Amino acid sequence: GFSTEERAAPFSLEYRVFLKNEKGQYISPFHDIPIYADKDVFHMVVEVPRWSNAKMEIATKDPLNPIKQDVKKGKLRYVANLFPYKGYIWNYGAIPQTWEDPGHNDKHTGCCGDNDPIDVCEIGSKVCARGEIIGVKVLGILAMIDEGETDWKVIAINVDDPDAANYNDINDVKRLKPGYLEATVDWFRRYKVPDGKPENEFAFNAEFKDKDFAIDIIKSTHDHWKALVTKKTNGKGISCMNTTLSESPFKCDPDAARAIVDALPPPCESACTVPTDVDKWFHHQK
Amino acid sequence: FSTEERAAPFSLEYRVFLKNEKGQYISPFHDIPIYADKDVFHMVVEVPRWSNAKMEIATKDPLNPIKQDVKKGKLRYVANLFPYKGYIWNYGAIPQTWEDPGHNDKHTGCCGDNDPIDVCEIGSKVCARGEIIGVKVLGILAMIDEGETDWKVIAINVDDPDAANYNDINDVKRLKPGYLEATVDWFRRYKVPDGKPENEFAFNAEFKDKDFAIDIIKSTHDHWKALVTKKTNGKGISCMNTTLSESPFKCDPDAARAIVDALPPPCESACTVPTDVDKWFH
Image 1: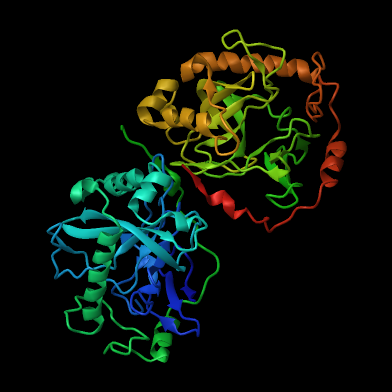
Image 2: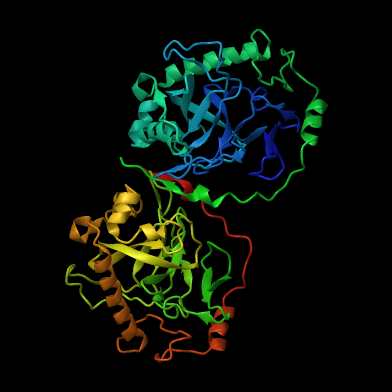
């Protein structure tokens, strides 16, 4: 359904991954990819493949949401290998046309939105690619508190997984992939510890909520997103520019999108070398 | 040392041969001295940390190149045992060692598994297939595999920035907590995803210390010596080599080169690693 246009070399500061539809029009992965792929099937924008380390995400404040690599203190960011794990333990990404409005306090957690699309942890066997669009069955949700803010972690599976029919709610994950949900909480708890930050906290005693609860949350975030691109709520720095939303004042001609991408350095097929330190293991007393 | 690869990575005919600094082909089983330096063992790296292809020195092939294992007609890959990705250490062998079957271990009661001694290297750098490094030996684990004894040496790359901190098995326990527990877990459960059990250990699955390990290693080096001087029958082991003057099996450089040049030529693009390799096993 979709394709990728990459500017500059992977793992440089200039690297940008833009999205294209079937006709070759540049689109925002944040705004132009429909939340649903089919009945009961959500789209997922894949940001980081399982077992990779580069911290890539949809650029919420840059025109045309590209996916790009996070930076702190001037350095390209890579997540730790938290022993016994290698990098990211699932395919990781966002559900498009979702937004955690920072104006909205969540009732269950008491905190406000983090201003980002809702995050998804995809648990299937296939290792997906950066920028790939897939369809997923939602299974459950985790409520992490990320520095005072509500940060939902949706648990899901690629609808095209050979075993996908066996997974319909969160209990199937406990049953068919034991230790997995436990590892997920552990990972999100400790992932910033090697950066000299404390562990993260969770609502609901770091328990997972089921499918229906997850889908309720996702629906709300989609309604908040509706308000965003339709200009009935303060955008708050977010770039709403899009290429397909008829009902949006922020819609733009495909050639204006083209002008943005072309100002950027050309596609460089050869990735930069990932620093050697990234391969290090971070152990801890358990 | 450097590497000559033949054919396409992850095909049946893929082979990695070793060369010395002068470009002469050598056996990684027989021609690399057991010692890099005083108290420093050479290790032939077979398998990088986090990879799955089950590659090993071919004990029965001329010049003992590294190649991929084959069971039931299929190229072997180890499972991703959940929570792990592939092999959790760099994995390889100490050269000029041989577990002689027909030597029984006193502590174990089982006989040798007919291979060089195995090494789990625990440093931070991911090493490459075919790489020769130097390691400090720290301890040893004894796995019981089919009536045979199968030693697993614990070691660290002597060039690891932190190597000076590691002098015995307790240093691992203190500096890399969880590591040894995970090693036993891995060795216990790997190959449960294909077939059944395979989980037994001597010594109640404890790690013996450095001095115990070095005694075992020296022991297999002595048995290796007999092998290549033909004072013990290899029964199929290829002892061909190019540096051992005391060996009836020494051949000249051109002879080794002819053996290598008979394999398919080097190939750039790898073969496709099967997608089923990325599955997790819980």
